[PDB]
Image (cartoon, rainbow, N blue to C red):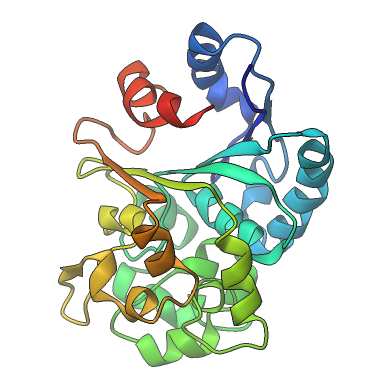
Length: 268
């Protein structure tokens, strides 16, 4: 009746935070087998994203192998990046709807409670001094910290974001793009009132200019050069932009309305 659904959580989380989401799905698409993966749950979510990619991969392969008509993915916050990289590196995934639930798809660049707690002596404009070090790149947040004022160090040091975005050339960029293009739909959810993702537009692949002007997905090389299939996906009608103004970063997976508008339609 419905394709299996895999959920990938974000920072300091577990399947516990998705009880409301599972309800929504059960109350609308009865019998849907939803697997909310409890991998890298509490502090382990701070592990390098590439590590998380392999872990999730090992866990997701069996589920996909059993899904005759493919599976759907709902990846929340940081999880969105793990999933994008995952769909980029496995040439045999069968993901239909890839729902990016408010993820920093084009990176993060903002002061946050978590950030201040983790780095008590740093601001957004300072973080790069730590995040772009070899050991810094061993911390999940740092793997996608995108400082628009140190773009050269970023392209140089980012071991995750700059790489999956094709901002830094690597031997398998073409294959990764080919793999990501296998997706059926790239559902982008996010909104102006998410008070964490910064810029919040990062959810729609929008990002800061060197002057901190928020450019649209289409005004960036990542798109114009079609580095990982954004342009191909868009022209094909695969990207579903679903903005929402009344949701804070913690409520995207606990809002019946959002679910009904932006998620339910894509869970075939």
